[PDB]
Image (spheres, rainbow, N blue to C red):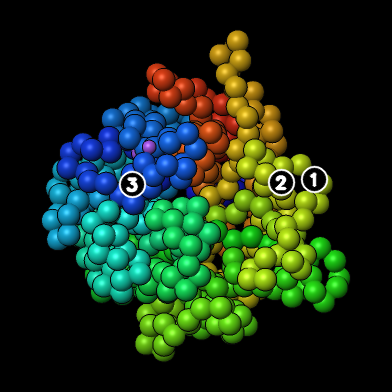
Amino acid sequence: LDFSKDFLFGVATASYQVEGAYNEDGRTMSIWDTFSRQDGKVYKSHNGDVACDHYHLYKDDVKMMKDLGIEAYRFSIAWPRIFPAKGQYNPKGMDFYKRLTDELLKNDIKPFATIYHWDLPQWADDLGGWLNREIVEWYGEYAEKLFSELGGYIKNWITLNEPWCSSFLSYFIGEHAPGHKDLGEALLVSHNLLLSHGKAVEIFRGLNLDDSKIGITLNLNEVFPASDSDDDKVAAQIADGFQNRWFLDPLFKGKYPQDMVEYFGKYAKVDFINDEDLKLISQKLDFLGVNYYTRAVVQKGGLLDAVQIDPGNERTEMGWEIYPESLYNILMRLKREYTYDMPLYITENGAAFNDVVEDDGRVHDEKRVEFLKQHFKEAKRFLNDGGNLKGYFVWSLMDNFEWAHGYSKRFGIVYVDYETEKRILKDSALWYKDLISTRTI
Ligand code: NA
Ligand code: NA
Ligand code: NA
């Protein structure tokens, strides 16, 4: 077999992107409910009030996954369902994740739970959010409650999804909630996110849950200089430090990357760095989840102003270059520089294309079939070169709410007709079903 029977073929979603039921069974608003109601923040003022209605349709969706042969399901847990007010636990919110995970297990699907996938409760943001160091304790209490109530259901835990997005994209670029534009704030948020991750790991190890694993998920790219010039080499180094090393180094080396500490320090405070915090941040993990989509080609441009070059190759509807070799290059880089023999999962990879249901009732998404084929071939090549890849989760199970793009970008292997909430298997889902069945590519 190209992929062993123990290899996990998975799919992934996130709570606010698919669940809907935004005001039901005690759920209160997250920063994204609020953000999507602010004019100009989200495409056509789309929001996740209803999304895919997965909260109500979860049994049908699990049956769909079973019929595809899905072996693992990565989802996130909505903090505002579990603690809809500070210190106020909501058993009805917990009950959803129990019946969801009970359904998954009874259909032979391994649950992978993301504790935080960007839907911070509005009550927490009103108290300062990720800028308030006290969030470390709020997050730890939330995580401990999940570990204690769901530890018999879920054995694979992910603390945070893509902390680069929750920090720089949300507080510096301002495209994501809460939408600040302040480099110093983004840097502090990145530190408090990592410290909160560390607190959850410390709680996790103290519980000593049998056969349970914990990790984190990072979106990673590969940065190419546009030319062999020294200017473009420095630009690539900064861009690589900004996207990848700012998170990889504290997690796996116990130290922020010094070139970036000095670079950022020309523009903002970096005084949050201290030894005690970096010891918590760098606690040993059981696995690393890698979210990979594309590379960047950069030339010198100013503060983080590298011009992004278009190398003229095929792209997705996001404008992201289709460059499968960087999946292998990034996995090898981790093996050789950061994670060594530690298990790796691809916790997201996928693509947005202009999907259309044709008169035959089918979605002939050939470009997504070819995209996934090329990237799974690179995963296979990593394995046959000795990489410790344990699974691969396609983003996404279904079309969903794509953050600032609303519903205009479709990432699913399953098409959702939002008017009816009908699920339509795309050709990529049928291709994936065959890959799982044959384990051959
Ligand atoms: Na939602
Ligand atoms: Na809205
Ligand atoms: Na580790």
Q: Residues within 10 Å of mark 1 (few under 14, many from 20)?
A: few
Can you say which quadrant of the picture contains the C terminus? top right
**Disc number lying in front (3 or 1):** 3
Which residue in the protein does label 2 denote?
322
Task: Give neighbour class at mark 3: few <14, some 14-19, many 20+ (Cα, 10 Å).
Answer: some
One can see residue 419 in this view: yes
Q: Upstream in the sequence, badge 3 or badge 2?
A: 3
**In the orientation shown, which residue stands out farthest toward the top?**
359
- Looking at this view, name the residue that lies furthest to the right: 228
Q: Amino acid at mark 3?
A: Thr
Which mark is nearer the camera, 3 or 2? Answer: 3
Distance from mark 3 CB to nearest ligand 2 atom below 8 Å: no
**Lower sequence index among marks 2 and 1:** 1
Query: SS of the residue at dot 1?
Result: loop
Name the amino acid type tagged 2.
Answer: Ile
Q: Which residue is mark 3?
A: 34
Residue 236 lies, in percent from the top left, at 72, 69
Q: Which residue lies at the image location 18% right of the left edge and 39% below the top edge?
A: 25
The span from disc 3 to disc 2 (Cα, nearest Å) is 33 Å
* Mark 3 touches mark 2? (CB < 8 Å): no
Residue 15 in percent (x, y) is at: 36, 44
Label 3, label 1: how many angstroms apart (C-alpha)?
38 Å
Q: Could you say whether the residue bearing mark 2 is in a helix, strand or loop?
A: loop
Does the CB distance between marks 2 and 1 fall below 8 Å?
Answer: yes
Do the residues under discs 3 and 1 have CB atoms within 8 angstroms? no
Give the residue drawn at x 63%, y 42%: 318
- Indicate which disc residue 313 carries: 1
Q: Residues within 10 Å of mark 2 (few under 14, many from 20)?
A: some
Residue 232 pos. (x, y %): 79, 70
Q: Is mark 2 within 8 Å of ligand 1?
A: no
